[PDB]
Structure formats: C-alpha cells, structure tokens
RNA sequence: CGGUGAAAUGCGCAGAUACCGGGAGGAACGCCGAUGGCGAAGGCAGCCACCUGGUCCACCCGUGACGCUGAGGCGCGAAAGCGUGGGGAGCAAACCGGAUUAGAUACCCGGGUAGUCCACGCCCUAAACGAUGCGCGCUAGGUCUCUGGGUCUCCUGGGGGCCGAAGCUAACGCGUUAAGCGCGCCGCCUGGGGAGUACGGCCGCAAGGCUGAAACUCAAAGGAAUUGACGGGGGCCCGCACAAGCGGUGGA
C-alpha cells in the first residue's frame, strides 16, 4: 500500500508532486482506495488535491501504456 | 527508395477491420496497409489472421524503404490487437516498444444507441 | 461414448510379419468378414512389390502409411448462425486410421483389374509421394491452411 | 473506409480511411466514485471564488412551553411539451433511403428536422416508489459502513445498510431507519368493466390538466403463497441422441 510505504505528508499541499505521483497509476488515473491505503475522509481529499495539481500541469491527466 | 530507417507503427484496431500505418519519427506516414486492402471484403477483416496479414504486408513495404527499428502504437480494442503486434515482432523489424493510447473521453459526446 | 473414453481394441499381430499395423490394414480390406480372403490380397500384393521393386514390402508398407497421415484437418462448427471450418491438429490415433482407410478407398478406385494388384500399386505410388492416397491427403490440408483464417476457436 | 448474423444504403482518385501539426466550436465532465454523501421532494457529481439554505457534535450558558399537526391559500415541482430569442458538437420522434421478412408501415445499417444546451416566461404530470403522511415516547442484540465528542483496544451522539428477540402480518415480509406497543393531527379507499371517461366548473397560448359521476354489464376483479407442468432460463447427469465409424433405404 502507498500510505504504509511513505511518511508524514500534507494531504492538502497540491504542489508536492514527489508525493502525489505515488497516488497515480501507470496511467494518469487515480488509485482506488484499495491501493492508496487511505480512509474515507483521506481519499476524499486526495481526490480534490490531485484534481488541482493536474490543472497547474504538475500531475498528468492521463498516461500511455508501458511494459514491452 | 528514400532511406528512412527506424520509425513508428500505428495499429488501429476495430470491431470491423484492423489497419496499420507506418510512419517516420516525425509522425509522417510512409506506408499504410489495411485489411480490406489485402483482399478480404467483409466480416473477414476483424479476423486475427486479417490483422496478421495487414501487419505483415505492412512491413514488406517498409523494408522497401529499409525500415529497421519501430515503436509500436496501438489504438482501440479489436479482434486480434495482439496478432498484428506479434506479427510485426517477427516481420523482421526490431521492436523498440509497444505503446497503447487508446483514446478515452472523460465524458463528452452522448454516444449512439448501441453504446 | 458419454461416460468414458472407452478403451481401444487391441489386435493380434500378423502371423507372417508380426506387425499389428499389418493386421489393421487387412481388417480394412476385408469386407463381409471374409478375413481369409483379405489376408491373401495383402500377401499377394506384397509378393508384387518383391517382383516389381528391390525392397522388403514390410518397409514399403510403413513408409507408405507414414506419408499419407494428414497432420492437419477441418471440423465444421456453428458459431454466429454459420458453418465455420475450424482447422485442427489431428491426434496420433486418428492419423493411422485415416491413412489405412484412404489407402484402401483410393486403391479400389484404380483402373486395374485384380484387387491385390490395386493395393500393390497404391502401396508404391504412395511411398513415392503420389497417386491419390497422398492426393486425398494433400487436399485436406489444402483446406487446413486454406481457411486458416479461422484458427482462433 | 464504414457497417452487419451476413450484407447493402453512404463516404473515397475534387485523393477518403489510418497518421502528425494547427485552428473553430458545442456538449459533457473519465479516474477518485462506493453496496458513499447531501437535500422536503423533484433532484445533485471536472476545478475556483463569491453569495446562500439545512444539518450534526461538545459546553449546558440564556429564554421559559413560546409546542404538533396542518382544510383552503402560497411556493417548489423529472422527462417530454408550448412562446420569444440565442445556440447546434453528439445524439435523434417524425421524415429519406438501406437490408431482414410470407409482409415490416419494426427490431439491424446510413442519413436526418423538432428536440435535446442557454435566457426569460408558460406547462405541473409521473412506477413524482421506501408503491410505506408529519411529530413525540416505549420495546434484546449482532454486524458492516459515513460522520461528530470522549479519559479512543472501549464508551457516547447522528445517518445509511444487512441479520435478528418480543411483537405483527393473508402470506412475502416488517423488526429501535417498524409493517412492533401507544397519543395527536391531516390525506385517501368502500366489488371489476364501463372511466380517469361523460356532464358541469376551474385553470392553460395550445397540448391538456385538476375535480369527476351514472346507465349498463359481469360474478368477478384482486394479493400472497402451493404443486405441477412449461421457458426460444440456469446448473448437473444420462441413452447408438449427435459426433466418430460400417453398412443401408430413398433410385431399378
């Protein structure tokens, strides 16, 4: 899980890309709660947060496929 | 002859016909081969064999220009997306890597009846 | 066969040569259980190979069989409200059976008079890779990869 | 190229399709997103800021019964639909053609106008459904979950679910989110069909809507469960039932 392999970080700091990146998939998509390892309230916020970081082009909106 | 080694292989797969198009680094189409172009005319094209042929005959026109390396691109979900790739992976072309950028709308055009 | 694969009948090798392959072939010529007649056919057809070729008929026989065994075949299938010829890798058992049979069906279609004769010639033209025995073989395959457009079922 | 079970209608040598770059515009808003949250309902999902309602918890501080319901009235009221104007990417009644078929005024395919998006104004209906009026008290728990307070491996408040005591129910089911035990207050029912019609009035630009009978006619209409059969429903299993094979009848 991503919460377990990571430390103390602000859920609201929409700039910190070095962190958020771990919350997106191999594609641009946002990890599901099963992955992130977050809570009900926690995820709700990460949603809003990335949705922001995206806009200031710090986080993608979508990626392409890799392995091959 | 025009001598442009190393390029791109766009493979457009559908539920009615799979087509290839080969391009130079910049994104310009060198040679392109469809299914209906081989010889097939209908239900036939969506066959993995059709894709196979589309892909193979598609490299043979590319070696014509001495194409050596290629980055593979795949669009959509068709019957035999696989076969065409696996096809070029043996056509005689060095495959740099496979890429999927199947186009997905973040919700826009209210699609038609059969969704 | 619904409950099991059912065991495969085991035969008694030939009294002459001793290869069951032989006994299997003869069975195929035999009509109306006149197995004493079909026995002869084979033997006298063998003797024709001796006089007409400098080779042991025992060997000739196997190599002839060996050559008509189609390794690819069609088997119709209803998918989409249609008959789709699905080509398929034939098993060991079904080859040997298809061979012997065709060898025969083909033989009796020869212009030749005497039965034993017909076998004799079919047994040779077979090992030489021709006649019809092999033709009824190459034709099926000429459907195998002819409609290989469907080997995905 | 497209599209289908197959196909054709259509689009392409004025060069389509597939591919790169650029520009316009409309609609909608993936993932997160849940068996979740919110709201009186209808309904509500990209992001931001402003304006604004409701609500929950803790403290127990203040007023001092100031409460509940609620005929008529007033406002809100999906979709479609009407007026004026704007807008029009995609979708698409009607309509044009294509194939299917005994035929197809359909189901499938290609086009396509209203419409669908916006503003103002009208319409006001609905499986507008928990098919379950609003408010207060009382009656074992278990578990999942949203959310708040606490001395936070446990306690305590509010919401959404599943199982379940007592109890109830025609039965299915319900069961501290009551269909339980009780009080208040409003609405509505009183055999089916005829009818949500007729007539009358009200409302509306129109489409229509609200209210709403009877004659006649039938002995039922109706709910839930049972047992069966049956399904071009499901799972599983058999037989020379198919397959595989040999041999035949159909011919004379």
Image (cartoon, coloured by chain):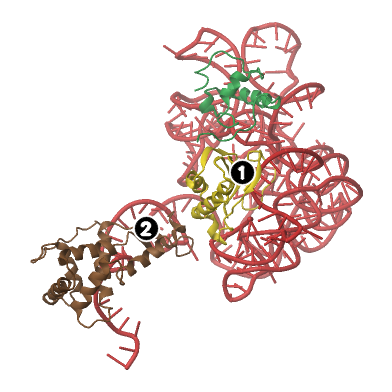
Q: In terms of secondary structure, where does tag 2 sit?
A: strand
Local packing at callout 2 (Cα closer than 10 Å; few below 14, some 14-19, many 20+) is: some
| Residue where numbered disc 2 is placed | C88
Q: x, y (%) of residue A51?
A: 66, 27
Image colour assigned to chain C: brown
Figure check: D74 above or below A23: below
Indicate which disc residue B3 carries.
1
Q: Which picture quadrant has residue C124?
A: bottom left
- Which chain is indicated by disc 1? B
The answer to whether D201 appears left or right of C139 in the picture is right
Q: Which picture quadrant has residue D40?
A: top right
Among the chains, which one is green? A
Q: Nearer the viewer, mark 2 or mark 1?
A: 1
What residue do we see at 65% from left, 46% from top?
B29
Among the chains, which one is yellow? B
What residue do we see at 65% from left, 23% from top?
A49
Q: x, y (%) of residue C38?
A: 15, 75
Figure check: D241 above or below D40: below
Q: Which picture quadrant has residue C32?
A: bottom left
Q: Nearer the viewer, residue D132 or A42?
A: A42
Image colour assigned to chain D: red
């Amino acid at each position: 899980k991503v919460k377990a392999t990571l430390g103390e970080f602000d859920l609201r700091d929409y700039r910190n890309v070095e962190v958020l990146k771990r919350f997106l998939s191999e594609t641009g998509k946002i990890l599901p709660r099963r992955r992130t390892g977050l809570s009900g309230k926690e995820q709700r916020i990460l949603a809003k947060t990335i949705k922001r970081a995206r806009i200031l082009g710090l986080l993608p909106f979508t990626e392409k496929l890799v392995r091959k | 002859k025009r001598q442009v080694a190393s390029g791109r292989a766009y493979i457009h797969a559908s539920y009615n016909n799979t087509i290839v198009t080969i391009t130079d680094p910049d994104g310009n189409p060198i040679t392109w081969s469809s299914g209906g172009v081989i010889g097939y005319k209908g239900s036939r094209k969506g066959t993995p064999y059709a894709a196979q042929l589309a892909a193979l005959d598609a490299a043979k026109k590319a070696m014509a220009y001495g194409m050596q390396s290629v980055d593979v691109i795949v669009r959509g979900t068709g019957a035999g997306r696989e076969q065409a790739i696996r096809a070029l992976q043996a056509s005689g072309l060095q495959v740099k890597s496979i890429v999927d950028d199947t186009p997905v709308p973040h919700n826009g055009c209210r699609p038609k009846k059969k969704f | 066969a619904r409950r099991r694969r059912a065991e495969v009948r085991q035969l008694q090798p030939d009294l002459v040569y001793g290869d069951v392959l032989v006994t299997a072939f003869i069975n195929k010529i035999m009509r109306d259980g006149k197995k004493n007649l079909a026995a002869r056919i084979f033997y006298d057809a063998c003797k024709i190979i001796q006089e007409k070729t400098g080779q042991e008929p025992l060997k000739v026989f196997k190599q002839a069989v060996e050559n008509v065994k189609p390794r690819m075949e069609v088997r119709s299938r209803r998918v989409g409200g249609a008959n789709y010829q699905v080509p398929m890798e034939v098993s060991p058992r079904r080859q040997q059976s298809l061979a012997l049979r065709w060898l025969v069906q083909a033989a009796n279609q020869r212009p030749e008079r005497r039965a034993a004769v017909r076998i004799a010639h079919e047994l040779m033209d077979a090992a030489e890779g021709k006649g019809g025995a092999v033709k009824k073989k190459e034709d099926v395959e000429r459907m195998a990869e002819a409609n290989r457009a469907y080997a995905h079922y």
